[PDB]
Image 1 (cartoon, rainbow, N blue to C red):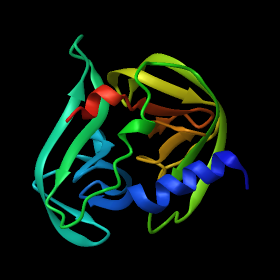
Image 2 (image 1 turned 60 degrees about the vertical axis):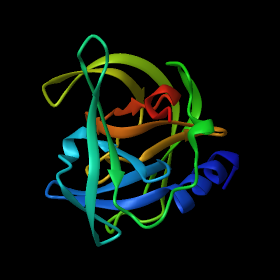
Image 3 (image 1 turned 90 degrees about the horizontal axis):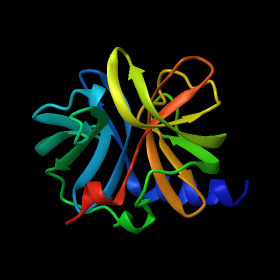
Amino acid sequence: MGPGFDFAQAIMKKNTVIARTEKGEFTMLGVYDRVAVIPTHASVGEIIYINDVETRVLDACALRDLTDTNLEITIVKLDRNQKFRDIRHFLPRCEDDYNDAVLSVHTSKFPNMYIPVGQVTNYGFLNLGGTPTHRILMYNFPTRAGQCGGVVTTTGKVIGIHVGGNGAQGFAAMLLHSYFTD
C-alpha cells in the first residue's frame, strides 16, 4: 500500500524460502550465497525441506552472544543450486529502536502476509519459552502461531526475524551486519 510494504515485498519476493523441519513450516530469510537464517526453535537437522525440495544442510550454527546467552538465530548453509541476492547492506550495524516496521510471512498456511506492527523497541532481555534470550525487539501487535521466521523490515533496513509473542506483543531476534561477515 505504501513505502514500508514496498520494501517488505521486495525482500519477500527474492530473499525468502519456505523451510520445513520436524517442528513445522517457517519463513526463512536468505541473506547471501547459500546462507539463510531461521529461529533456533526450528531444530534444523542434517536434512531440511526448502520450497518442498529435500535439501542437505552443509552447516548450521545456533548463535549466542559473548555473555554465552541464546540469540534464537540459527545460521544455515544450504546445499542449493542457486544463490540468494546479497542483502547484507540492508542489515543494521548496531542494536537500535525503530519506527514504522512491517512483519512479512510466507508459508503454505499464510502466503503473501504483511503486518504493519508499528514502533519497535530495543527490549533486550526476554525469557523466551523458558530460555534467557538477548537482543530482542518488541512490537505491540498480537502475533500468532505460523508467523515465526517472519521478516521485520523498515523502509531501507532488514532488522529482525519473528521468534515469539505473549498474545498482546510480538518479539523478534535482531539481525546484525556482523553475523554475516564473509
